[PDB]
Image 1: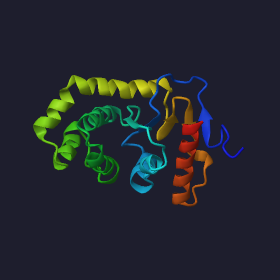
Image 2: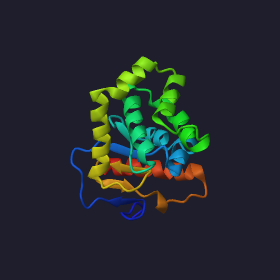
Image 3: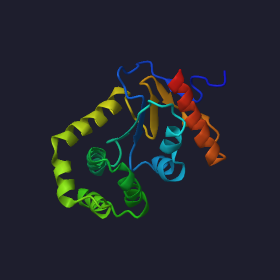
Length: 188
């Protein structure tokens, strides 16, 4: 066929019931994730091709960056609860990987403050039980697919995107191919 298991995607021998439709994992420590966010706009280009009624979910993971990596998962939980994913994603990627000014939870907080989230609002979010369970959903979803690498994408808890099997000579082509695959898997 044109789309084949093991080529543009793999299938989970252990499907995950009740999974979000399009589920994406990343880490602010993850160099390809940096590329996926700032250079390729993968998440974006996927959305643009997904049908209507598809909701898109993105989660952060713990297994990179040790203590900071967990802080970041909690921080991303804050961003989700406050709905400010789009104002903190870039300064977080760049603070971790570009400028290396993020070394502690406090520096993570600074990104939020600079992006205009109130201190009061951040610290209450950070410490809230709504963020604790948001943290738990993130960890659970990663756990459910035995996630050992990022970036990672899953469609309907049964398919996992396989970017290795896509041509990378042209960035725009990689992106359209990646996205089209998601759409195919979506309709499967």
